[PDB]
Image (cartoon, helix red, strand yellow):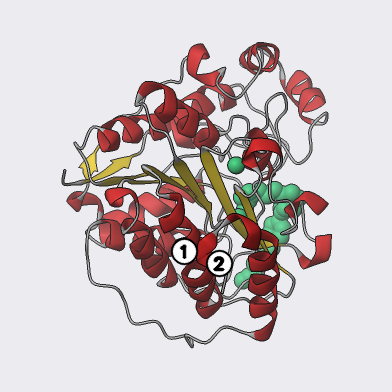
Amino acid sequence: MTGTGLVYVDAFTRFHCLWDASHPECPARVSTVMEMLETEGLLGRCVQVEARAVTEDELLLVHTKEYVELMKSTQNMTEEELKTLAEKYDSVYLHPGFFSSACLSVGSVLQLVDKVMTSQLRNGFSINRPPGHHAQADKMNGFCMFNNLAIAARYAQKRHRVQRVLIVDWDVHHGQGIQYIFEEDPSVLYFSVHRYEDGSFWPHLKESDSSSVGSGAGQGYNINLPWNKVGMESGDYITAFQQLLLPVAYEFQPQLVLVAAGFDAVIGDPLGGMQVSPECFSILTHMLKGVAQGRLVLALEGGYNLQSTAEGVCASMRSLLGDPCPHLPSSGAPCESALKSISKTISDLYPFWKSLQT
Ligand SMILES: C#CCCCC(=O)Nc1ccc(C(=O)c2ccc(NC(=O)CCCCCCC(=O)NO)cc2)cc1
Ligand SMILES: [K+]
Ligand SMILES: [K+]
Ligand SMILES: [Zn+2]
């Protein structure tokens, strides 16, 4: 059970925003990542895995046949028809090749799920766009068309008999799509740390607060860690993982870990406003390898500084390949605002996880 998978196809670069040449979700995001992985010698050390289109059967695991057909109906629309449909969604652009690339974006994750759950690879990383963690059952959202990881979690449960999936969302934006799809599901534990600022940061939702601990059977299986001050650094995330996610992770005992690996919380991102060094994601990735026998699959979400995102992917890739953890320039001590958000989240999840009762 050795090797690290890497999935990248040029179709990820064959769709862009037609009415805005400076849109941050651009093909240069994934192309700059591949360049740095090659120049740093990391790309050659990975087992290249080919992608595949997601079937209508797999897409229907979280979406509706109506919405899937409308998204399929977008490849034959004109630009005026793409723009009038996109305007019906929140923060979304469309393109005749968008739907095609989105299908390869979803299947790229499932390809790694196959190889990892069959012990052919130890872990994997898909360098894919469009992102996915905002896509919902019958609508696009936040540059996403289809929910890559939410599909992959249900796919692994059905195709590979997995009972417990852990989804770690370290993107700077709350993945409200994944939270909605699994709001009552106790078999898919969704953790999200994100910028919130009491709701003044997009998507400006109260459901992104720590008090949305899931409902019904999934009561306690949705953990939101909302930041409320910008400038969070590596010590805030390390403390967050060590005192909140990892204790709940070992108690949950998942058989597969899927990471919404966005990098808009890295230094210099135009949107995240956070101060996390890229080397920190070598530490966060390393922590996640002690869970689920290291069955770890990462998929690109956000990250819009071309240099910051590529550095984050590279730092994550070094941990996947087993390279030594890096020296972190930032202080391992968290800030007071982070401890307040960590404390409040521990309180909202205290009655559901014995590892937090302290
Ligand atoms: C050196 C030096 C200077 C560098 C400074 C710089 O260039 N700043 C800068 C700022 C803005 C832009 C945008 O064009 C732009 C437009 C619209 C939006 N929409 C939204 O925010 C609301 C919803 C967003 C979905 C997020 C998806 C996601 O990530 N899910 O994980 C965002 C950005 C480009 C550059
Ligand atoms: K997040
Ligand atoms: K859940
Ligand atoms: Zn994001």
Q: Tell me residue 249's x, y (percent).
A: 45, 56
Residue 35 appears left or right of 208: left
- Report the image quarter containing ligand 3: top right
Extreme left residue here? 2
Name the residue tied to disc 2: 356
Give the residue type that dot 2 points to.
Answer: Leu
Q: Looking at the image, can residue 204 be seen? A: no
Q: Residue at x 41, y 35 (%)?
A: 109
Q: Secondary structure at mark 1?
A: helix
Q: CA distance from mark 1 to mark 2?
A: 7 Å
Mark 1 neighbour class, 10 Å CA radius: few under 14, some 14 to 19, many 20 or more: some
Q: Residue at x 60, y 46 (%)?
A: 25
- Relative to residue 299, is residue 226 depicted above or below? below
**Mark 2, other Cα within 10 Å: few <14 / some 14–19 / many ≥20:** some
Image-based side of 187 in relation to 222, left or right = left
Q: Which residue is mark 1?
A: 247
Q: Position of residue 20 (x, y in %)?
A: 71, 42
User: Tag 2 or tag 1, which sits nearer the N-term?
Assistant: 1
Q: List x then y, in percent, for residue 54.
A: 46, 20
Q: Residue at x 30, y 43 (%)?
A: 6
Locate residue 41, reporting x and y percent: 22, 59
